[PDB]
Image (cartoon, rainbow, N blue to C red; front, side):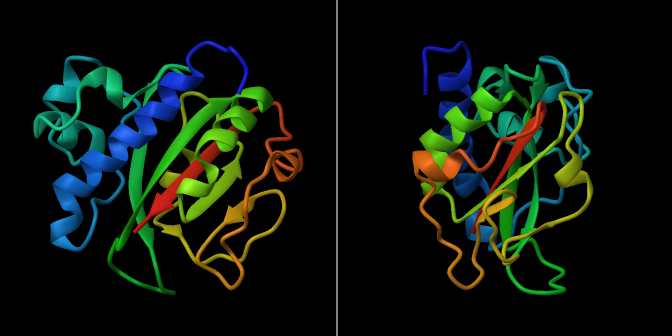
Length: 182
């Protein structure tokens, strides 16, 4: 991406969070349910005990508040469950949602991270909201298309998100990216 403020930090945070999520939870074989981080502060990320994943990671000492934050939206990063089969009742994956992105920010982020996640989708969740995560566990096996469900565990779902392909997405004025992994 271009020399645009904050995008490199958010991208790096996605990596840092991935490492921390694996360290905290992978041994359990399942990941935490979504709880909204949208009212957290730099204080309360250290104290909230309702099950917000970034708060858990900070309280485990595996992450700090700046590493948990989306500086583009000004929200702490949303993290919820993801499923790996139809009608599963276990979060066998996790999903993180990056909200409040301009077209350029969204494209830049996809150009840096896209092919490092086995599920990638683009939505329209604004700053202050996590529309995908609040809707439920993310379906990692939804069929891909060229605009919304970009990479998934569906048949032929590990699409290479080249610069050219990224031109077909992030096309709204307000965009969001959901990344998910086993």
